[PDB]
Amino acid sequence: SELSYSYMTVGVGGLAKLDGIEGRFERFIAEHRDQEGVKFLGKSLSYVRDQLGLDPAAFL
Amino acid sequence: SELSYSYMTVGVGGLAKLDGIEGRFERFIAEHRDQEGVKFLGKSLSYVRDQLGLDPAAFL
Amino acid sequence: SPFELKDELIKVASGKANRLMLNAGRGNPNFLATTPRRAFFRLGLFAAAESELSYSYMTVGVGGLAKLDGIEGRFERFIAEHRDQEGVKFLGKSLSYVRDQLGLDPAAFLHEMVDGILGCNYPVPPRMLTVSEQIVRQYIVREMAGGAVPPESVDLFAVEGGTAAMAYIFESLRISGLLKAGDKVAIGMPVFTPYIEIPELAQYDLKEVPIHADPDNGWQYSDAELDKLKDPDVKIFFCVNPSNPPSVKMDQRSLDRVRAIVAEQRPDLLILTDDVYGTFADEFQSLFSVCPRNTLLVYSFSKYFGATGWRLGVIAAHKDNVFDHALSQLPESAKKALDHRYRSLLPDVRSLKFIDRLVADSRVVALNHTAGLSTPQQVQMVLFSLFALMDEADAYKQALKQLIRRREATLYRELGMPPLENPNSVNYYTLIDLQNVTCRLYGEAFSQWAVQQSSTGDMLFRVADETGIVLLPGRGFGSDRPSGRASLANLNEYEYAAIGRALRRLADELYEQYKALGKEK
Amino acid sequence: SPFELKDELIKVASGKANRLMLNAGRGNPNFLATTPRRAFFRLGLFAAAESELSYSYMTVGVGGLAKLDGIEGRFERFIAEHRDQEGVKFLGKSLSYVRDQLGLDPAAFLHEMVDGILGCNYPVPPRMLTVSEQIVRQYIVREMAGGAVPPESVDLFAVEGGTAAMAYIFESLRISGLLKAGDKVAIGMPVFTPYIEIPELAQYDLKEVPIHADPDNGWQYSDAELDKLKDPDVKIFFCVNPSNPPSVKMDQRSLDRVRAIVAEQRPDLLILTDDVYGTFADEFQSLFSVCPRNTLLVYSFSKYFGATGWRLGVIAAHKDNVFDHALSQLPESAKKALDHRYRSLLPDVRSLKFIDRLVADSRVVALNHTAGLSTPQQVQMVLFSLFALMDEADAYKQALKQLIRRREATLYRELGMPPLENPNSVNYYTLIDLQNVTCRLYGEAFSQWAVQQSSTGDMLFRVADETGIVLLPGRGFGSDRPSGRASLANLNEYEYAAIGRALRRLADELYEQYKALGKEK
Amino acid sequence: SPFELKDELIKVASGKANRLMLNAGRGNPNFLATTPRRAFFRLGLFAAAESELSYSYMTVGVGGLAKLDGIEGRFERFIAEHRDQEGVKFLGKSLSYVRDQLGLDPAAFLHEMVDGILGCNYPVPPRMLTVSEQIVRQYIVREMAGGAVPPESVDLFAVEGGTAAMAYIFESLRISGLLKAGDKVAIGMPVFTPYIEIPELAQYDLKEVPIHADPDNGWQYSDAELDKLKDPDVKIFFCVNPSNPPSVKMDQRSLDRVRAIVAEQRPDLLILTDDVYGTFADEFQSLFSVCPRNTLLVYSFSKYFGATGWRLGVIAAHKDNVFDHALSQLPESAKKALDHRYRSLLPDVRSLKFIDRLVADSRVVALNHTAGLSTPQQVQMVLFSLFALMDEADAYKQALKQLIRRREATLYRELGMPPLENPNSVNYYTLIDLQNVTCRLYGEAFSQWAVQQSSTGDMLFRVADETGIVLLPGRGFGSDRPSGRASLANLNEYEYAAIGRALRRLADELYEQYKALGKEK
Ligand SMILES: *Cc1c(COP(=O)(O)O)cnc(C)c1O
Ligand SMILES: *Cc1c(COP(=O)(O)O)cnc(C)c1O
Ligand SMILES: *Cc1c(COP(=O)(O)O)cnc(C)c1O
């Protein structure tokens, strides 16, 4: 969100774009693989994608 | 550039590929969100993309 | 004698280094290309993580299959977060080269590499992993040929190292008949024991045809000698270029001839060349260069990158080669026989390229769809290739040369300094010749005396006793000279100097005789 | 029909996953043991560094040979400085186990591993790396036998995966004669296409002897059927335990018999068992258990650890086995013949164990001293072993079972739920039987009607058309029932459910006929 | 024809790379010097911080002017706190070199660089930033001259790239009259389209005087041809050294002559040399070498450092040059005219050096005090210089050479291998000559036939159609040979090979005619 709000204002934030979102989610995941929550927050994406076979990006 | 010059030579560097460039710019941005310049270098991308509505990748 | 000789030699031989020399008549490089190695391990680390992030349940040991979608992005991330490590810096540029110079599908390339290193899938196709073939083939056609061959015209077969390469080729030849029992096979010599023993088998029973290399002219093959292939009953030519033990490449003359013979009077000729010591040389043209449609090129990654243990090699073969024509000029009988064999493979068994058979042959056909080299190996091999394809200065190649020159220097320090630098010698092996040594140490006089006073065998045991180092004999002369074949790539500065310390210690024991037994005159 | 069938199936088959099933009649695991994998890459990283710190000149790419002196200390350091990474935590305990449970030379073990992973030296001995053999053999005798066999009595041969294991064993048998043309070979059935094709070759020309497994009794071999081996002219027994496609282990009864037969009336019998699906099972006894001196055990690391691409396997063989006795009860003629062959190997060719030949045979003897499996592979394989030897809870084994049960559940959700849980079934493969399915969905009435209204072939294409998934046929019945063989280890939850969505979509198309065509009555 | 040719070529031309070639008859380097680039960005980062720490109020965006006092200390600090980054390591040594080899005011140098990169002040003086001139001039006199010229005697003018350099020089010549309408200008040829069009203008209306380069003698200028300058009515000489498209330097002979002519019979001669491709060459002497007082040296940083987009160049000019003498041998009329023009500049307008005018001319005098090249650019250019001045091994220069040799090799792999290595060729551009190609592929016979069967234009379109690559025509022959001018610096290995794949695909289409149409004889 903050990276979608185009002006230089601190509190505000915009709408998350959908294009290229797996890549980004993926980045976030690797940069935090240490935290107990993100380890799971990742596999979920697998399951939503590899077992339910749904649109990963959509899902995210 | 350095990551486009295919031989093992230190000074040289090649031409920036356009494919997948938002992802990368995005990565660079998140890994430096601390520096006063990159915080802005990011929002610009929004504005070029969300307000002027231009080809983000092209722009980058 | 030279079978009970080696017998008691082992009895003293100290090492493995010297024991392999003694058992396989080859030296195992005490050095190795590490950069591609690190890149490999590093690539696995990234791969390992892709996998864990594809196994959807909460279980620690398990991991799934790497997805292909979005993979450049990720590889790219991994690269930037580790740009510090010596291996990943290279693991990145490779991607450039595969993409910006070979112009291949980057993503495709990556996923083949990633999945390839996790060795979690059967080699598809068995012959060799799609891109790995386009990459590694590029390495070969450049070092070996470079001259004519567009890489797009070469086919490769991933095999467990030259060794496997042979046991595959021969057997394959016999299975199909491109080679019938009692055929004439030309053998460039001198060659090391092993190869002159594959034809000397029962399942082959073929006949030798030495093609002697002229010592007095730097172990080059004599114009005459090469003309023997003119003889229309000599089915195939067997060469190791550069040669082992000589350690030399076939000069422009040597090549040109075969080029002609094959071209003028022998287009039916088959060539099986083992051009491993090939890459060491500054400039090098392989028989596969001059006769691309009549040759079967065997390259082993083992010597140059110190990677013997990986067992990495390829069997190169043009797309329009005789081996495939010959499978045509065959009696309609055998054809329909083979068609019963390769019946599971496909519908038209008469379209099956030879190269493609070597494969099917290797694992008794029926398993074909599970034959091939391990995906990890294919990957490592690829990495070793791009490491060579991107070392534009040859800093690595330059480094080894000098590593030889030095081992050379040290060896001969106490034996009349090093020999005449042969521009076609690769020096992987050096020939310590007793005569020549003394003709440099004391003079033409003394020389002749000791050459008759001592034997090769005394040399080889005198050294393997004082030091513990095995030295190969001088095969293919007039059995008239004690000579010593040392490898300049399997030992350290202090050991080579030790070799000399003995050879010279002994060249003095003699001189003290020629001296003391002369005063009786 | 079943050769042009597969023909047009491929024409629609979507994948590689399904394409291998179709081509090799086997499922490639969509999962894999990663911990040992990470440990591997991590081990290389340490190895890489040992090497750079052994290459004495100032050159970046090059690296030398790992010294053995002081190596535990160093490995220990590396371990403590990385205790954070998932792989090194395990890479450490291994060292314990190799040292505190197997009681082997720790340092020795390490240096073999380190040097082994840098694949910079030829596999010495070729058969299998010293400690790797003592370790990996420990894995085998425990899972496969466990009963009698002291690991110190088993010999192992490192080969490129089961596949290689066969092409080595058979050929080796023929070379030496423990198998003569026109012999009787017992084949436990049903088995998948490939294996019943190796004997059906020209270089063998042997005769089949099916040993049918009784479907109505969970694909177990019938007492009678096994008695055929009593026939003194049946030279060897060929089994795959657990079976493929059945996917079951030979119960205590089945074993006991062979145990007797062999022991009472057939101590001349040879056994070649492929016990890969062996490890999946909770408890499992391999034919190598009961008849250790008459069996040749082939184990492949490929299915259990998802490591097909590594091509890792062993050929187990007791030290006192018939294969070696039989090489004695041989005409003095052949003996002196073999003695010409294996002449380079040693002095007394009549002492050469069979196991040891399989080796020499594999690369046309003369190269023996360069044959064997890549040192990296040997290492990985070892790591996969200790990973299994140290998973005391079986958390990994438990994890896969459940991964099967689930894929099972999902598949049969819309087809009358899962079958009767067979305590001897490993379920790697499931049998979707049209009859049984409908007798659970609609009733004995409807069943009989559709079984005659549809064929296996319609099933297999109906599915491979709606989804894109290849399904194996039901080999070995009365060709009287459309059945479907699905693998529970090569696909994902959503795809299996997709299989069902079709099978059931089709089981309704029929029911709407039995319904609508009944009202005309 | 060659204007509607290019027309429909664009219609197919795929790229920008090939589109610039086509539009400017020049190749844009697909490579670039990055180290100086990083140093630049890094320098700005330090500069940015100096500035914020000079803006005394609490406002985030704003920043002030970098103080000069104590600046080495600070730069030094910044350097030590970043010695890890590839750019700052170099950004430091530069300071040494500027201080320990050129012996200039370190602090001065730094502050000019820092303030220079923040581009917050007008270029003072407009001609070129004080130290930047002393540094960058050092680069020029060394590569270009090196022979005589003490750098302290050269003057430089910072301009927007060669391009600007011309439009400045010519116009400047006309404004002042050192060039009057209808003068004779000598043009070394062949040259690319653009330059032979500046004189062909209305605001100039001058006359051509080709000075042909002899193809049969490697595009060198023939003794005779150069003698034309002897003609006292030829006001100036226009050369591009090395030449474009030929890509060669004027050998020692060529130079010596002009050296003489100028010296013996033409000290009134003016020389305008564009020595950009100058630096690529191993050793190189520029016309500015031999005739320092009669030449105007134009150097562009764009090709060598891949920095076309920066538009960086200089106009070198001795301190005692004719251009300044000539402004004296002028009618007292014009003099007092110019004195009205350059009236704002100073008191004595007859002291104004030519170099200094080029400046004033560039922005319609009145603005002189705001003309010049951007301070950032001046800085980058300086950094590119010191990067060249400190690469003592030429590792960069060596790297590009090889990058050419390789692109060369790849191109000609399927066209009779590469041409005769010319020691004066820089190879930036290669000449694919249809004749020569076939005389290497098939023979003198075939050659002559196809040379008349095909045209340059078919070549250029055949390639730009199969691949999408634009190829320059062979200007300046007897319009008698299809030739192809490829640039070895604007494409990748896989594309050049693609060029060949076509050229050769086409050299076979012909051979199949000479072959098939010969059999009718
Ligand atoms: C050592 C060497 C090679 C390498 O054999 P691999 O299976 O590839 O290990 C090949 N041929 C000869 C003559 C050699 O000296
Ligand atoms: C898949 C499987 C194996 C593994 O073969 P590898 O060479 O070891 O890949 C062995 N036998 C059967 C019956 C199989 O199903
Ligand atoms: C490309 C090139 C240059 C560079 O021109 P810039 O303004 O400096 O971009 C100069 N002259 C010729 C002949 C060229 O080929």
Image (cartoon, coloured by chain):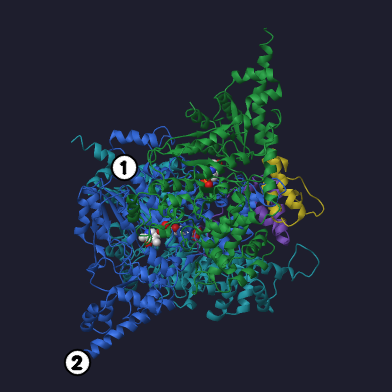
Chain colours: A yellow, B purple, C blue, D green, E cyan
Q: Secondary structure at mark 2?
A: loop
Asked if residue D52 is positioned above or below residue A27 in the image, the reply reads below
Q: Position of residue D51 (x, y in %)?
A: 53, 68
Q: Distance from label 2 to label 1 (Cα)?
A: 69 Å
Residue placed most toward the observer, C137 or E284:
C137
Give the residue number, with chain letter if any, for mark 2: C520
Counting residues from the start of the chain, the first of labels 2 and 1 encountered is: 1
State whether label 1 is within 8 Å of ligand 1.
no
Q: Residue C177, which numbered label?
A: 1
Q: Nearer the viewer, residue D140 or A14?
A: D140
**Residue at image x 66%, y 60%?**
D90
Q: Residue furthest bottom?
A: C519
Chain under numbered label 1: C
Q: Amino acid at mark 2?
A: Glu
> Pointer 2 indicates a residue of which chain?
C
* Three-letter amino acid code at the position of disc 1: Gly
